[PDB]
Image (cartoon, rainbow over all chains, first blue to last red; front, side, top):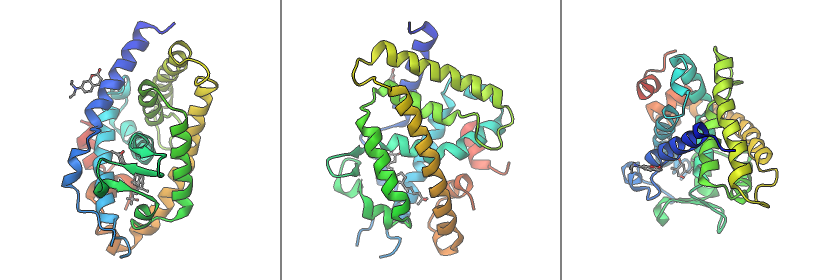
Length: 240
Length: 11
Ligand SMILES: C=C1[C@H](O)CC(=C/C=C2\CCC[C@]3(C)[C@@H]([C@H](C)CCCC(C)(C)O)CC[C@@H]23)C[C@H]1O
Ligand SMILES: CCN(CC)c1ccc2ccc(=O)oc2c1
């Protein structure tokens, strides 16, 4: 059954996500304004959203049970490599099938394929990014499953540069077993059918999304006029 | 390793 420890983990991750994810999107007023007039028009706005979103993912990560027993260097390696992935996962909450967009409360803050293009990216990222969002949306995850998936993604033992892999694995295992066991006990069929394996598949799709983004990001940022439009946190975390 | 802002947000 679902153990007391496993119930505790889920309660922790729910609370952590709620503290780091404002479904009103009120802080979006602090971002440089969006412009949809203009090459890289949306880059200041979306650089800021991502920089904020990075901070929030760190604030989530810190509250993952076990995460803090990790050295600071390993915490750093895990956040640096997962940040884009967790922003992709956490964005599914604003993403809407109704029109294939991220809907953050108001027309001003509603982002589509054209907007992400006006931030320096192409369809080689955006198309499989949208398809990921659609496949993840169709799983109709319980918020419990959502927060566990983000957590499992942050604490991945294979990320390069991880010194204490075995501890990262043991931490991830606790969360994976919590998730397998939660699906079995609380997610009724047919929605539960192979749901775990479909969740892990999404982690594999995210590796490919990460790679592509890193490469488009390298190309974008090498141009010192675009790197000017980013934030210092985006520069340190994604690279320079 | 030279990640002052990340290390700050993590402390
Ligand atoms: C709070 C949140 C999430 O953290 C982020 C949200 C949406 C995420 C999006 C929508 C716009 C395009 C985004 C930002 C993607 C885009 C390719 C990031 C680009 C970052 C850059 C620095 C320009 O390379 C990644 C995730 C996408 C809204 C909302 O759900
Ligand atoms: C009520 C105190 N806060 C932070 C505002 C939250 C926010 C979200 C959750 C979400 C789940 C939970 O168990 O506790 C929470 C507390």
